[PDB]
Length: 525
Length: 44
Image 1 (cartoon, rainbow over the protein chains, first blue to last red):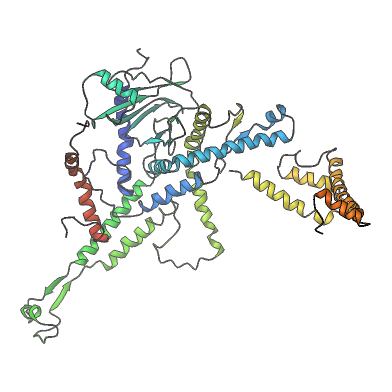
Image 2 (image 1 turned 135 degrees about the vertical axis):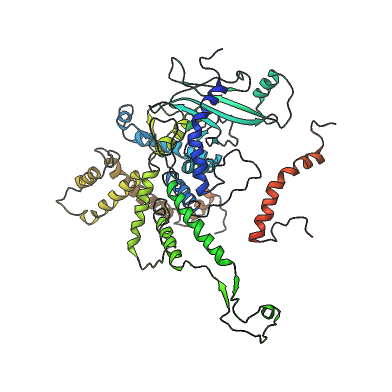
């Protein structure tokens, strides 16, 4: 049908004239740091990428993309599923069932970490974080599993997608551009391309578009793929608003523009000035590198004898005729060096590398004083804080849906939500701290006055551990007092009759021969 | 049979003109680090 917005190949073309501000920023912004990261895409093989004269942008990007990956995504359990605790108390008989629910929530949070690591999501997120530094603005598509086989996720680094969003935060429509070759197309698309007509080469590429527009009269998204034809008839997906496999990530958020900025465009002016120094220092060393022999032409020394002489010949002439053209700028090389060492000093804090070689340095700064490296962690804490909303939560809310449909996860009952805690964490440390406070109460087990039954509740109240699996309740002890007794009942009892039977089993020796026959032993002993 | 793509000796020759960007990069790129690692292969 007409499908209320048309056409998807032209929605990409109307809004391709909106990437061109951000795209020509990133082509400039990758030129100074690392040119292989975001090409101009009027680029082929060959177009060799000249290294920038400065190597701080190449340094301070890998040292910032990895320190985001190490901080956003540690190897352990970076998400956790909080059940709403008061609504968990109502629907359940306390207290054993409550932690039994949290074992099912500890079940799921390990399966996702066994799903993320076993599908190389760590790879394509690190390729995402390098795009988020240089350009921002990457959407990565999480396809349906269709089995327990290998399932990566494809990203699109702003030269292959288009989104359009509001001045308000929500997304209106997305267009992604593939260039899948004809032999490599999926099976339903090859029926549509052949259904369009005309034979194709095995290696000819096809601009395959998607269109993920927000629906008329319903809050969910509609998603249809297309070719040069209208649709592909495997198209329509009813993606809900909160769970769509296409999520556009965003380095630093700015309203109400459609895309996001990047982090390293906020220092791209400063790299532009630091390369212009480092271009000049190197070129001053190249005039230096040339060795010109200035012969004083009012002198005696002809170098017709200086060249053709051997290892140690005696030659005519004065030494003060032969001087060499040397590069001047002794007091000028230090001006351009001390500024370039000051600009690298104030970019090395902007990026998360430590203060390092590029000074005298001269540390004596020792030894507990380098806890001010935590100032780099706090400055790092301001960097990804936007990104934990934009990437880190929608990547879980998609995987909580897609694993329900493929039955690789239990259907969690509509009430559990997740924070991206940088990981408990709070459940471990608050349990570990109240143990040591209760361990100080150990010499008070014989004190007749202190209510140790209450102090252990007060520390469990001061430290915010919950309660009610925390202490033995009213009944709960007559069972426990019996178990020490039933132990000593079974212990003294089994030691009684075994001494009781075997003493009288062998006395008046005819009974000893009768006792051995019951086991089946003949008269051996 | 015809095997739907032909011939394999010419698929190598059509696309040998696509290595020549990367190949002449690596011949330059090994020249500066260690020249024994990637020869020009007009080399004996």
